[PDB]
Length: 163
Image 1 (cartoon, one colour):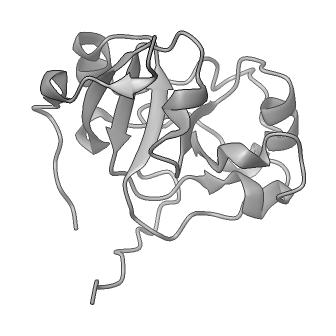
Image 2: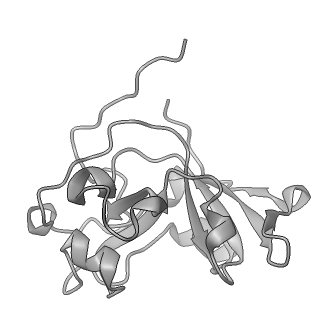
């Protein structure tokens, strides 16, 4: 039987940009307390992501309201991930399925409900993004079949297991 997950005191321990202001998050965030693998579709290549982590577009002046950010894709302090390994299949054009093992994140559907138009994305929004140490690796995606090119997956040399 699997054990329970470590719980960090800092809700944005994972942040690649610690300037994120947690008190500006609206509505009141429901933080993810599980620690399973999460995923992110991204067209940016692993040489970049493994060096930088996932940095958010705008931690200072971006859109801190999660419902707004989910509905209308504005520069924000958040990096979006999903609980769903297979969500990459519904992404048009996104070259890679990144694998993430990071503490925390805001559980979108627990925070804004599961009846909004994108509830099927089962999103976890990371305020301040995600340091490279929490990015496990990546698999490229074959666009025409919407499948992972599993012999071309790559592990992140900077990944640091923590549980």
